Image: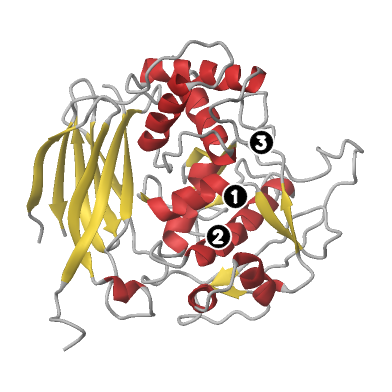
Amino acid sequence: ENLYFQGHMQDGFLTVSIIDATNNRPIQNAVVNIYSMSSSTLYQNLRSNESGQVTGLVLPAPDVDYSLQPSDVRPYSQYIVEAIADGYETVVIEGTQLLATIEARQGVPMSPRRQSELIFDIGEHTLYGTYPPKIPESNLKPLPPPTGFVVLDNPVVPEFIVVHDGLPEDSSAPNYWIPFKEYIKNIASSEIYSTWPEQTIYANVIAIISFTLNRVFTEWYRNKGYNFTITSTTAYDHKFINNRNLFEPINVVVDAIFNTFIKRPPTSRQPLLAQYCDGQKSQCPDQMTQWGSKDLGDQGYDYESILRYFYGDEIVFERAPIVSGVPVSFPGTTLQVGSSGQYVRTIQNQLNAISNSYPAVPKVIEDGIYGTDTENAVKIFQGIFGLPQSGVVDFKTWYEISRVYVATTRIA
């Protein structure tokens, strides 16, 4: 006797992206099967398109209401996604998590080669499952003295994070090189539900970035003699799940503010080691509660006041330099039809390169004039990587282009 009948299901959406793990190139015409979780078929023999994608799948998901309050019911569905493709070792993803009204994006990296298969398993979301609580720890850490290079004396967004999938002291756990923005998206997809108010996603993603960039900037684990940047566990850091699916509302937020962080006191060099907790299973004062920032989201607060409410009035928001592996930075003005010059020529040069791996991206004359041709290439590109198809190269589209350009021009 809930709102409806117990068992009621809504539509949540899915897009599957199949990429060759050795060169990041999309795989076309792979088979994609979907199953449920007891387990039975739902979709059979889906074929990936020329961008390696099968888009717009529709899958049942619990009532969205279960993800807007603390609940005993799992607020998301779990599915199995199977990718098969000739020449490639098959990949099964178990536990792909679907939220009603929202697009889940599942990435499938396949390696080239007989009867072996890769199984990635996605555990329970931290807001639902039970995970070891976060070992308490100080918010500010010691630093080496300033070398006087200012960019070196202050946080910069690295290009990669080296994640240790296990406790720090378990030397047998694997280390993965994750691109920064895919890292933050993976943490956020397990820490919050993307059916949450926009301003609440922003404020939680900035806490995640402050934390993560404090591990990077203080070189926490290297100066303790480990060969990694952060671990995947909830006790020392936050829950990272290799190849879990990301969510569209979270991806667009991160694309937009992935270099923004908290400083407290405002004179800090290092970003605040911003810590949180859900706020039902566990309390944590002087810090942020995930469920508590949802309330303030519901009550219409913006993100600077959500964070200032949990961490204090005096905090300031900083934007860190970004190493993207293209030695040009976004110039601070959106490029669009009409624009001209070297930044436009650089966009067109990157998109043409990308289009050798993603032929859906039509080619453009590389002349430095942002014409209809370029706006159409940017709209198709945006559409492939889950971005609003404004056809406009603002900050978030700039670094997404650089990210794919590098990912596909790296080994081949």
**Considering only order in the chain, which callout, 2 or 3, is on the residue closer to the N terminus?**
2
Query: Are the two marked residues, 2 and 1, in contact with CB atoms closer than 8 angstroms?
Result: yes
Classed neighbour count for the residue bearing mark 2: other residues with Cα under 10 Å, few (<14), some (14–19), many (≥20): many
Quadrant in the picture for the N terminus? bottom left
The reply to whether residue 326 is visible in this rendering is: yes
The Cα atoms of the two marked residues, 2 and 1, are separated by 8 Å
Q: Which residue is mark 1?
A: 257
The answer to whether 96 appears left or right of 153 in the picture is left
Which residue is at a point 30% across and 81% down the rendered structure image?
72
Can residue 240 be seen in the rendering of this structure? Answer: no
Quadrant position of the C terminus in the picture:
top left
Image x and y of residue 353, in percent: 46, 16
364 or 46: nearer the eye?
Answer: 364
Q: Amino acid at mark 1?
A: Ile
Contact (CB < 8 A) between labels 3 and 2?
no
Left or right position of 343 against 371? right
Q: Which mark is residue 357?
A: none
Point 33% across, 80% down: residue: 71
**Distance from the alpha carbon under mark 1 to that under mark 3:** 16 Å
Residue at mark 3: 333
Mark linked to residue 202: 2
Looking at the rendered structure, the kind of residue marked 2 is Tyr
Q: Residue at x 80, y 45 (%)?
A: 154
- Residue 356 against residue 57 in the figure, above or below: above
Q: Residue at x 60, y 79 (%)?
A: 284
Foreground pick, 70 / 273: 70
**Residue 30's quadrant in the figure?**
top left
- Say which quarter of the image contains residue 229: top right
Of 48 and 34, nearer the camera is 48
